Image 1 (spheres, rainbow, N blue to C red):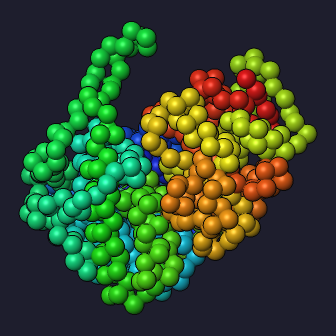
Image 2: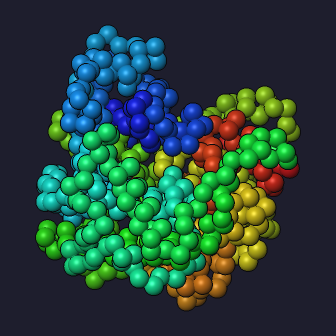
Image 3: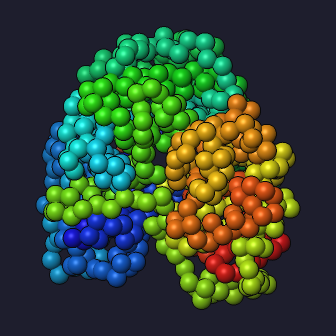
Length: 566
Ligand SMILES: NC(=O)OP(=O)(O)OC[C@H]1O[C@@H](n2cnc3c(N)ncnc32)[C@H](O)[C@@H]1O
Ligand SMILES: [Fe+2]
């Protein structure tokens, strides 16, 4: 079957994306933000991403067996907004506007329960037969947590937790409270490493062997003037934090900056001042989730754990789940957040139609790619001089080994918030100055934010304490003693790291580069950070890459077979 999965809607939505499954294989998958260049894909149908998906696979909407949306939108409208006003045809016109998606007739339209979509994005793509399912996000239509059993190609829900008790919303609110912003929870995770925890309950949570209770909020609380509990939980958490924490909310400041010639947004206080709150929030999240995970594993009799929902992006937490006595194996897809419910919805429907879903297979490279002619057009367009090295991978390795920072835009764009060797900025893993250089000089981002490494899978048994694939940088682990001091820009003082392991099959070019690098500096390991300007999405097109390259003080750009230098 050919099934197009979608997320994103014009009204109060984020993380628009589209994924196309053909006979159980991912033909194409991308996030709207990569095309619009507007981060988070807010308040939009995934128009560009779905257009890309069909173009990639050489299909039109008339070739689809089904279209799937990763929320029960009709139920949300009916229960929260006073009615669902759209026929399937009218809904399709919104999701897939006819001016971009000409169609003779309407494909079958399927709405999939949000947490089922999240669950399908983990289970069906994991390459594992069965396991316990833990979904933790902000909120679906109603619930913020789902515990389920994945087995026999089926997903059976065991229990849920109502939205008012959301761990996702909690974490967003803390992030907003600290001035990092609710839209940047990844930053809160990074800040947390710098703080100390005193009381992980925050005088709000109570923990037990199956999870948590939130005494702060009535679990059945429901906003009568909305379709999720975000505002209600925001009001509760902000009042509580101000009452118990020594610092009041950080505030955003909008002022005209003469040097930039525009009004810029800043924070009133340095968010670093809130590092203890960050640490404490991370600790509460971890403890809550440890209990939920232990509980679903025990109830299902499984030792393989699937995690999805946006809280599953918390690599620090994931690392600590992996080492628990109750967990033998773990799979978290790169698209654990809402961006993955397009894929998840497509999978649930495809499975229902009798297809067998193939494993993701250690790669997230499903977005657009560009031929040498296409890259050349973007280059020629700008009039910059460039080279076509006989051995580009060897040359890039040499640049990295010397301490230079290299833009790397190769093959199909990776999907999800982390660069994985398709759209990356690369630097030395071995350099004790590279971290400060990239934060302060290249990206001009917070000094306290860490970096993480890519390495050959073929060496990771020697480098990391665990011999397993870590394809997505979604899970922390620790290095072995021989590597405790060798890799200062990407390994913390406590030996922890957030790796990508790279197989030759997953990414021949990046694998070959890392191999060359290893010949130069002993270890086929590099620093791998997102290729973007601050606050902007990862670059997608050759023109995107050249633009950001032009803006940042980096040494070179390897784009397709071409090398541009500053
Ligand atoms: N349905 C719905 O609400 O969106 P979704 O499934 O994409 O999950 C979003 C949630 O992920 C949380 N989140 C994102 N990254 C996170 C991180 N690194 N650590 C903790 N929570 C995180 C964040 O706090 C937010 O509440
Ligand atoms: Fe979600």
